[PDB]
Amino acid sequence: GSAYQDYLARSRVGEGLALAASARLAVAENAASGNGFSGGYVSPPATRNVDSIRVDDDSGQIVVAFTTRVAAAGANTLVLVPSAPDQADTPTARVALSKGAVQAGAITWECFADGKASSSLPAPGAGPLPTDAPTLAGKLAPPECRA
Image (cartoon, rainbow, N blue to C red; front, side):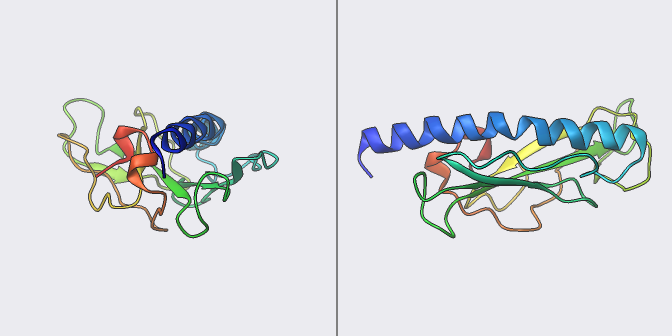
């Protein structure tokens, strides 16, 4: 769309990612206690811009679904992927979260928009890829979500 409409959409996407911070909190807390990653978490009520936020109970990946006010259906999602190192001193690689393991390491979050085909995570290594492909256009997402 126009420059202004893109600027408006980007600001609304940023607001939506702030709303997903509570889902990332829930995943991190559950990982620390060895519980399923969606335990205790429910999507916030829909806003004019964010339809829903969902947490996968086995990987902790989060899908943020924006409404058609932000982007067209099937072109509207961002995915947030959590990962942990193989060990917490000079780490060797990056692993997805494991249900039932107590995760002591810092958990790193990586955002993915449409067109980001690979993790941009540097050494200690690249992170896992979204299970459900995100479809929100990269120009509407923060830079760290973009290819």
